[PDB]
Structures are given as structure tokens and as C-alpha cells.
Length: 182
Ligand SMILES: [Cl-]
Image (cartoon, rainbow, N blue to C red):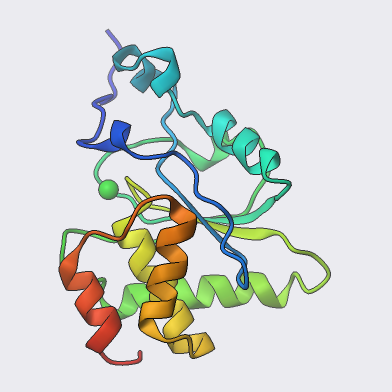
């Protein structure tokens, strides 16, 4: 049979696929869409493909202008397979430590480079990890705190309310609340 991993990440099925766009920002968070080979392991209602991602964005009357992918554990999809042409960036966010400073800067640079080129539209920066929750929430909130001067608890609350789930990792939360501006 074909070569290619296709295991469903632990807890992936448990999360709402796509959050609401965060008002006051151009962020939106989602869990990783899965390419076709994964679907052998899913019920139809559990599937969440790249097509489903774009459909759900459209349902909100929004449009992605950049995808930032934080994942590393498997090949989940190839950007060139996305059914809409959208700028893409991989930023590997590995393991469970607070994302390192290089990762934080690469995130900020990607966001800022997108914004500076899109001042006549409201296209979004879509950010995903596996669950679209922990690494995603951390980086979004770190951006808001550092770049926009948002109080950490206000960033976390906005992220949580829009995502549909609360940021879980306590070390991430603690760094947001008490760690340094990068
Ligand atoms: Cl991952």
C-alpha cells in the first residue's frame, strides 16, 4: 500500500475545527486540516480537509491572506495542494517548551510582512498548530502583547472566546502573563 503516515493526532477530533476571526485583529485560528489519506480513520462528520477550511472561512464572510503552519509531527497537507492560492509559511514549533525567541520573531516578521502589503483589505492571517490551540494561542497572544501592547489576560481572553476553546498549556499562559516582551 502507499507510503505515507496517516494517523489522527491525539485529541484532534475533540476540537472545533475553525475559530471565529478575532475582532480588533486580523487573526483567525484553526486546527490542522488533514489531507485525504487521513480520512480512512475518520467518520464523515469528523473530516476536516483543506477544502473544508476554505469553506468555513467563507462561511464567516472572511478570506485568508496568509497561512502560518506551526506543525512538524507529520505531513498533514502540502501547501501546494491547498485549493485556494494563499501565501504560506512554515514555522516549526517543536515540543512543549515555550516557543523560542527565534520562532516568536519569525512569527512577528511573517505577520508584519503580510500586513504591510495588505492595507487596502481585511484578509486574515490564519494560524494553525495541530489543535489550533496551544502553540497557536501562544504565538497570537505573544504578538498582541509585544507588538500591540495588549494586556496578556486580555489577549488570552480574546483568543479563547473566539477560538471556542481555552488555551490549555500552563507554561505558555505563565510566560504570556509574566514573561518578557521579545
Ligand atoms: Cl505538530
